[PDB]
Amino acid sequence: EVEETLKRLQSQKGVQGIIVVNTEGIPIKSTMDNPTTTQYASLMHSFILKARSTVRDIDPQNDLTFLRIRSKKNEIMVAPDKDYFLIVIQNPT
Amino acid sequence: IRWETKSCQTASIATASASAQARNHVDAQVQTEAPVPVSVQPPSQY
């Protein structure tokens, strides 16, 4: 079921890859090449920790809901969860 | 009328050299290791 929905997302014209980060920055599923698989998973793990803390710091009664990062090259979206988040990368062009 | 001549002598002494020194230092060197025993994507089945 979820395998089909992930493929469905991957088929979207914007999406350039999906990484399922599970073990604290170490993913278990990917539709991307190995260097990118680890690159995005690791970097975004560090970032989301900062983003979630940022929310707790700006207000001590709230957690993260979502983050978006945009760049000239590509755009990356992540959502927080109880155990682990998911990374999706799109080509804005 | 009786003047007696006498000679007196005191004992000698003995000294010894010695030294003092505060606590000593010594160098040290460390290099932090950067091990990364991390695979790319282990397909877990937890």
Image (cartoon, grey):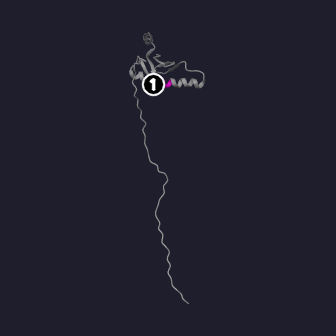
State whether residue B32 is above or below residue A4. below
Is residue A87 located in the magenta-colored stretch of the structure?
no
Look at the numbered disc 1 and give the secondary structure of its residue. Answer: helix
Q: Nearer the viewer, residue B6 or A23?
A: B6
Q: Nearer the viewer, residue B33 or B10?
A: B10
- The residue that disc 1 covers is A42
State whether residue B32 is above or below residue A18. below
Q: Nearer the viewer, residue A1 or A40?
A: A1
Report the magenta residues as a range: A41-47
What percent of the width, then of the height, locates residue A72? 47, 21
What percent of the width, then of the height, locates residue A13? 44, 12
Of all chains, the one bearing label 1 is A
User: Which residue: 54% across, 23% down?
Assistant: A52
What percent of the width, then of the height, locates residue B37? 39, 28
What percent of the width, then of the height, locates residue A21? 45, 20
In the displayed structure, does residue B24 sit left or right of residue A53? left
